[PDB]
Length: 254
DNA sequence: GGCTTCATCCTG
DNA sequence: CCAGGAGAAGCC
Ligand SMILES: [Zn+2]
Image (tube, rainbow, N blue to C red; front, side, top):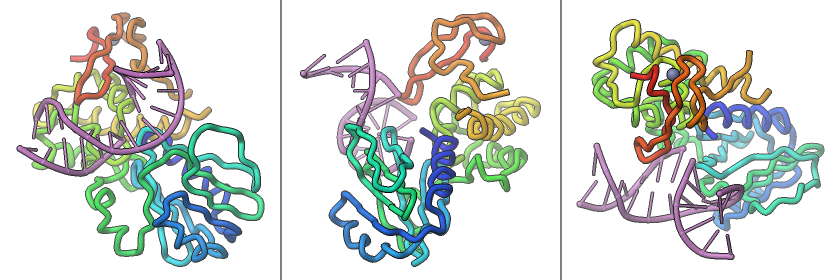
């Protein structure tokens, strides 16, 4: 799961328990158990996302930081229910009527206020593609910046320092949308291409965020190797780029 | 810039 | 069943 999925989940967590007094708090990790007593009777004030980083803010200025990597997943349950599963529970934030459970995640930390700025991941993530304040021409500026203008898109679109929230599926769907392979640099695009890329970097993630869980978002190439491209009819192929699987259409990506 | 590595879950 | 496959940091 990447940005869009994490924000959908964060929205579900806030709907479940934002503002509601915690009646129980449980952490699997021994070093976090000390926060159990401290948080009972506090409440989540909001669940912030910074790309794939999920920050659950509490009313006593603590912030639970969690990153699902490839395997973590949140689930909202009615309080006291525990749908059977083989995943290991890692976090329970429980209120009178709704409880949220975080399973499998291994990167979980309790942050004090300073660390919202200094934590290693939070310190180096770039702007969030789902941030409404983030505009195409800002993305365009960033693409052309000295920092990123010479990066191949293959790696750049996975680098959370560039744009937070982008992941593999988004990488392939964005590059296909604008007809580019992974081996290009922002410096060598024409202005039309650059403008198309800057818009797709935002609109595709925002589209997935709005509709993936429900015109609606669909993969055009991701996991479609062997199928005919819906734009040009060519057969979508699967290779490896940036040591991650990569899908693309040889017929209309150049 | 290329691994090498960690981490959990699912499949094949 | 066991191995490989599926986000980010580390060590050159
Ligand atoms: Zn095509």
